[PDB]
Image (cartoon, rainbow, N blue to C red; front, side):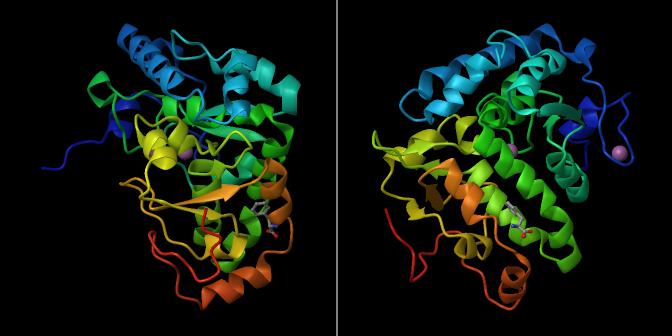
Length: 277
Ligand SMILES: N[C@@H](Cc1ccccc1)C(=O)O
Ligand SMILES: [Co+2]
Ligand SMILES: [Co+2]
């Protein structure tokens, strides 16, 4: 049997822009159970993350006044985010067209899936939800270097799309925004949103001998496959957000064409030039 998925169920009776896929955050659809699920997730992650998340992430939660006890009101958070870095968040139904996603980032708008997983799905949801998108991704938007990296990434979508290279950018996003690590004198820390919202990938990614921790290298990353339904086999480690921003400022066009004819690395491979940490 085919049954409707969670995105379809949650969005019953609601609409989205056929173009930019933005809707007003539907506050009246959050049930008491939803605010409780949020509070449970928020509490779980805030217990787990000290000494694991990078300091900028934890300070962003506080500076943005991300609610501990209910799903946040996006308008309220936006007042703080706008004053910090001129960003805002926009509600979307769930996954959106790539060109829309890029155009949002290019214009300093971060798309956030509005709805929340059900309490039976507390431990893990495959689809992004509001907890993953808001709690995992938004705190670092108050950091001006990281926010400029996202805007720059957004602006690159047009060139990538024109050259059939969106998957090569998607790999860079996955291995930075979603699953990145950042080294510090106090030890390795986490900045990827997919780790920061996870029940236990923050533990594996720092504590396990199993994954590879490889120094960031733009061409390697854009030539590396990833999988979405398993802990990462490789994490890429930056030294600073200023590195994402700088390492990723050259013209990507000749890089895409060189990659377009290469065979990519598997998700668990170690490449001959990898600085392995
Ligand atoms: N420098 C990239 C744009 C980009 C910036 C930052 C991250 C990813 C892509 C280009 O030439 O298109
Ligand atoms: Co639709
Ligand atoms: Co994400």
